[PDB]
Amino acid sequence: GKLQDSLDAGVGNLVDADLAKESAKLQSLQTKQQLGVQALSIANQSSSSILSLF
Amino acid sequence: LNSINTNAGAMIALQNLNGTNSELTTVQQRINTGKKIASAKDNGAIWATAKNQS
């Protein structure tokens, strides 16, 4: 019984993710994608100023 | 001088406009990457140190 517990705990240490760091990465990447969408929206308008020349 | 065959003022205006466009491009690129040193083009030495260190 104790050996089974040790093997299962070893599997858990081998694969399981640490959710505490995941909680910070989630919010950071949400802000990151929002900033990326904003920057791509700004970049899309580069050709709009050309019509003013004519 | 007021010939129709050339227009230097438009030439300097275009030079300044392209310079400002390049500055805005690099700024929006650092906005959507979140990194002053995005690639080896930005600055090779610290970028190399960052790659090895990470």
Image (cartoon, coloured by chain):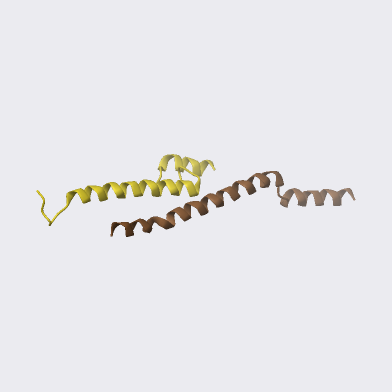
Chain colours: A brown, B yellow
Left or right for A53, reference B35: left
Image: A3 above or below A47: above
Quadrant where the image shows the C terminus of chain A:
bottom left
> In front: A25, or B28?
B28
> In front: A28, or A15?
A28
* Residue A21 image position (x, y, % from top left): 67, 44
Outermost residue on the right side: it is: A1
Asked if one can make out residue B39 in the rendered structure from this viewpoint, the answer is no
Left or right for B21, reference B13: right
**What residue do we see at 53% from left, 41% from top?**
B53
Q: How many labels does the image show?
A: 0
Left or right for B43, reference B11: right
Left or right for B8, reference B54: left
**What residue do we see at 49% from left, 41% from top?**
B50
> In front: A33, or B53?
A33
* Residue B48 image position (x, y, % from top left): 45, 43
**What residue do we see at 32% from left, 57% from top?**
A52
* Residue A53 image position (x, y, % from top left): 29, 57
Asked if one can make out residue A39 in the rendered structure from this viewpoint, the answer is yes
* Residue A17 image position (x, y, % from top left): 71, 49
